[PDB]
Length: 270
Ligand SMILES: *C(=O)[C@@H]([C@@H]1NC(C(=O)O)=C(S[C@@H]2CN[C@H](C(=O)N(C)C)C2)[C@@H]1C)[C@@H](C)O
Image (cartoon, rainbow, N blue to C red; front, side, top):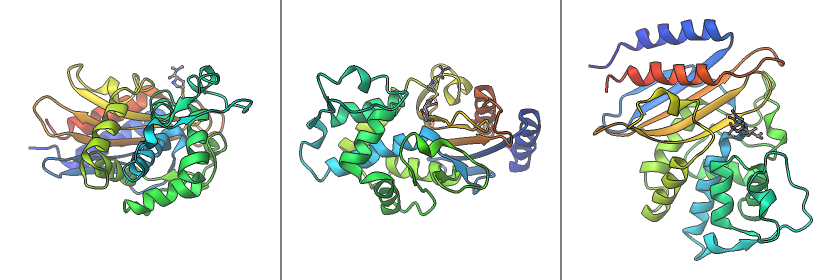
């Protein structure tokens, strides 16, 4: 009963032609294990979207270090990165590791990302090592939170593929690499993301549940979203949508990401 893959490809190519850039997608039906990809093994900049996996890396560490999520981190006199809306308000109080994780995922707080990278996960190298440890041999993080967003065509730094992003999200959400407590916490964080209203969430009926993490590099029309989607009485779908444009000075398009998501999800004929 699903749509022929070439129909879905044909629709995405027309969308690409309209957008004036490149669209890469991969989707997994976790109940039938049917999959769909388009440019699925092409590399795209992660932008801020790595932060969902950063939160996962923190939970993995906490599964081995009792009470890590409750540890308070203070950062008096630190120069905070732009787009740090949570951490810039909690300097006097400090934040716990759980609060920093929730902030980096749900608000795309760069300060929180770099705090967790510096103090817990071992920098871009350590973030990459965590992804290797779950069998993702594609992901790479090379730079810290601000600098990783240059999105230059041809530069493989701070990139992954739609396939690898979706496959790693499926592992973390539903597989064995995290314990039950940790899976549940990760999915609750994704469900409460606040930055994705115009992307994958905008492609699904309002009574479906979504957890997602976005990225918006701010250059080269480069932006993305990946998600777990729970349709009504259907197995969850994992979806990654990555985009870029050839011109440095172009703007990204939220609508193209929502439209690509819609095409892909409709192809499963849920
Ligand atoms: C990461 O890519 C950058 C930040 N992360 C994201 C994002 O997750 O999309 C943005 S875009 C920001 C959040 N949502 C706002 C929005 O949608 N409107 C104001 C319509 C804008 C950040 C810039 C990071 C490198 O800073």
